[PDB]
């Protein structure tokens, strides 16, 4: 199977996505980081362009909140499996989440999938095919799905479904991290860094 | 909805644009600026050269009048949502407006969209697709498109678009801010710096 | 309107080009220059390569006859308007002409459109589409049209349209300039500077 | 015939991949190394992003355990054959493996296909298209196939096929190496280095 | 009209090409060199890659046979006019002629048009649509047409059409230059570094 | 036609490609070398990275064997031909062979073609499309086709192709070589260099 459904893992997130117009999918990302040999973002396959765009875009948010500049480190991003036929999210919050995880060595809840794009301001703004994703998620045996707050009323769950996934609307990057990073002294420090 | 339409709000604005044909869409920008360890405009997409340009024109206006150097501070320009076959506007005023809005950190009326092209020396130059653009601001339920002046007569709106919206003829950048940049002490300050 | 058709403005020049396969359009153009403190030609959209070829060529000529070394300047060039399926003359001379005008800061006559491919050496080479361009010129109500002298047998106008525009042709850029540049001290002192 | 099914060769591994939207193919590779007197990774084709990626995850892994650095080496990789319609897997292990084989000088077992994505930490990640990666390797007469353990449930074989190949599930790049590298003094001391 | 049919001009050659595959056309070019003040080939719009290629090949023999390194110069090629539906020769001897011409300032004779491709060892190789081309040469009042020696029997002319143009087959670059460069002291010294 | 087929010229190697689907193209290569006046591999088009690969590999095996180093040469590598959908073998041996030719200044049997991938041990790896290649090599009325050895059995031929040609299998560069160099003193000196 292409993704983990529970446990905690560094630089590892289950985003969600769309195949064709039919349907949604579990889209899992690893991020890993190593210092550069000036610094680039490595990824390949049908999604590399989504990946440099999120990673690059989010990169100031990522400097306000470790203090590691991205151009001092190499960011190794893959998508786990292959997917031709898939639209992914712009500035996707999973790809930023997995990177912050990897930079910070703080693990991620696999049982919580996510969707949204990430304002360079740090907000999370709406994305297509939410119902179709939750749906893929309900199909995956994942437990909670984070989503943007303005897709709140695009969640057209057809009952019996209303109780098999916990749908969590967020609107900051800090809410996404709060809700998926493993508890501990590290995330506690981390969270406290989210302000002005 | 997806794109915001009520409120005021920082380094983010309503670009008008056109997917080629008769074909309007509302294209927001979102800007953000961070004083740097010079600096680099960071933006992605088919419309980076434009993000870059808008920004480059807009530092003359700001080192000159304000006397802020925008070379000291990395700048994020990002357009929103999935846009395909879009023609952008050279030195597009949505961006430069958002850029003044990041940097003097002062919100913008989101009733208001706009389109235009910013000359280094401050002008709002005319642009193609001025009508279909207004038609876009309309089925997106907005209050006021701002629009270049030399574009008035490229409005030729029909009965189902006539009186639906406030069109603002602008010649200068500061006519743009006069009209969208929210109110109080900072705007007032930014204004006088100019003349 | 996307162009001006009377008076003088700095750094502004109504080009001529062809849309699809019949017709002309006026290709209006602005250039502006600030010191760089070397520098670039910033232009965007579809016709950018032409802007850089023309500024690349104007500037050598600038350096030979005046003093001003475009080396030291950012030239910012725009096609007021947005031009798809439109196709220029290489080393377009509207463009070179708008640059020579931002730099000298002598305004240009808007009542006269033009078209020419500019050699590094200073000639105005011939260009495709004269007849049609001159028709578009007639159409926006522009008084004259400056063309490459070798394009003179290409002019195919119905006798009544020969009443409508002046057709001037030319073999060197400095002739485009007496022909366009605002009458003046500056302009004179400038014509002096291309004594050959 | 485009790959080998018997014997050991230095720096040659039988990858596995898909052509169109089913059918596996065996995807064989040489890597080779020479020093760089910096270092570059040399591969053409539709699959070379992958080749560059594979190698760049191997380096750090090798450095961390073996001490050898690859900045001071040029690496030359080839997909023996011509590979259109084909997607490889991210950072294929088969390439990672063929690089380790090169540098260390230890023959690889040609009768064992392998598929997988190597992570920078040395972990073996799951992949698209396992079954036809398996069918195709049977098709070629390979005796074992190494697959990412996390894909054990994707293995879908008819019994007449269950007996025809050995499915070996791994989760780490050192396991792959033990399972493929030729036996001997080199192999062992090499392993003592990943523990 | 777009080419000069007689006299000599620095860096100015009448190549031949084909419009679609109905007909030949004169495709006239100009190369011009300025110093680099790392060096480059500037050129525009439609046959810009034929242009970059031709030069990138001949560089070779620009050094090997004679004088200057073109990585220290900028090569500014233009096609005089505009070029859609036209098909460009590779490693074009008309470019190389133009570029050798501009560097030596030895004028090229405009009553002789040319087609063919330059190998890097400097044989001229067959090209396509030669009859059509010559038919363009003929049509356009150029006196003489240089063509590749392996196309000799691909020339299929009507009676009337054969005396209408001198046809000159060549097998090597130095013959093309023997043929089109202004006699005089400078060509003599150029031509005599085209040994062994 | 545009290519060689009996004969013995230097720097030139009739290789083999597929135009995409499976349609035999002879793809002639011209190599050329001069000294840097460090050095460079000077190629044009889609194949231009193959070239530098074929080159790269060949310098390695030359430095080793002959002792000669050719980091000093400026290498020119040319594709004779005009087709798109062009599809080349990695480290393609044609190029490897035109080059070794170039350098050792040694004429090639024009009457022979080849496909092949060359490794840094100067093995001949097999390549796909073996049968289409043997065909354009027939259509091109050539006498011999060198193929990689392990390609030995992707060889078919309906009645119409069988015994139309000396197909010749190889596993090493020095075979490729023994096959195609013009006999005598410099073949010889350079040959045994691969043995010493």
Image (cartoon, coloured by chain):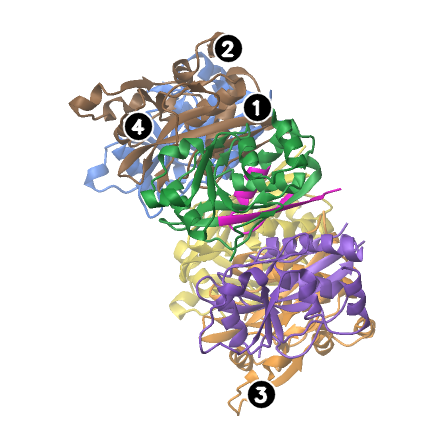
Chain colours: A orange, B purple, C green, D yellow, E brown, F blue
Q: Is residue A5 visible?
A: yes
- Say which of marks 2 and 3 sits in front: 2
Query: Helix, strand or loop at disc 3?
Result: loop
Q: Going by the image, does A191 lie left or right of E192?
A: right
Separation of marks 3 and 4 at Cα, in angstroms: 80 Å
Indicate whether residue C33 is drawn in magenta: yes
Relative image position of residue D11 (x, y in whole percent)? 56, 44
Indicate whether residue E68 is drawn in magenta: no
Q: Which of E97 and F136 is in front in this view?
A: E97
Q: Going by the image, does F45 lie left or right of B42?
A: left
Separation of marks 1 and 3 at Cα, in angstroms: 69 Å
Q: Nearer the viewer, residue F170 or E126?
A: E126
What is the chain identity of the residue bearing mark 1? F
Residue identifier under label 3 = A164
Relative image position of residue A188 (x, y in whole percent)? 82, 75
In the image, residue C177 above or below residue C164: above
Q: Is residue D41 visible?
A: no
- Say which of marks 4 and 2 sits in front: 4
Residue at the left extreme, as displayed: E159
Q: Do pointers 3 and 4 mark residues of a single chain?
A: no
Q: Residues within 10 Å of mark 3 (few under 14, many from 20)?
A: some
Q: Residues within 10 Å of mark 2 (few under 14, many from 20)?
A: some
- Say which of marks 1 and 4 sits in front: 4
Residue identifier under label 1 = F73
């Amino acid at each position: 199977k292409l993704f983990i459904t529970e446990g905690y893992e560094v630089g590892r997130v289950n985003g969600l996505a769309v195949i064709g117009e039919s349907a949604g999918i579990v889209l899992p990302i690893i991020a890993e980081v190593t210092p550069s040999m000036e610094g680039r973002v490595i990824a390949t396959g049908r999604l590399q362009e989504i990946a440099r765009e999120a990673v690059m875009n989010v990169s100031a948010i990522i400097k306000k909140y470790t203090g590691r500049d991205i151009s001092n480190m190499d960011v190794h991003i893959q998508f786990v499996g292959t997917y031709e036929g898939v639209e992914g999210d712009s500035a996707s919050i999973s790809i930023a989440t997995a990177v912050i995880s990897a930079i910070e060595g703080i693990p991620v809840d696999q049982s919580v999938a996510m969707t949204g794009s990430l304002s360079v301001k740090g907000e999370v703004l709406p994305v297509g095919g939410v119902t179709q994703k939750i749906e893929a998620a309900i199909q995956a045996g994942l437990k909670k799905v984070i989503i943007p707050k303005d897709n709140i009323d695009d969640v057209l769950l057809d009952a019996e479904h209303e109780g098999k996934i916990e749908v969590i609307p967020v609107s900051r990057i800090n809410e996404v991290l709060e809700h998926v990073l493993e508890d501990g002294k590290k995330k506690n420090r981390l969270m406290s860094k989210f302000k002005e």
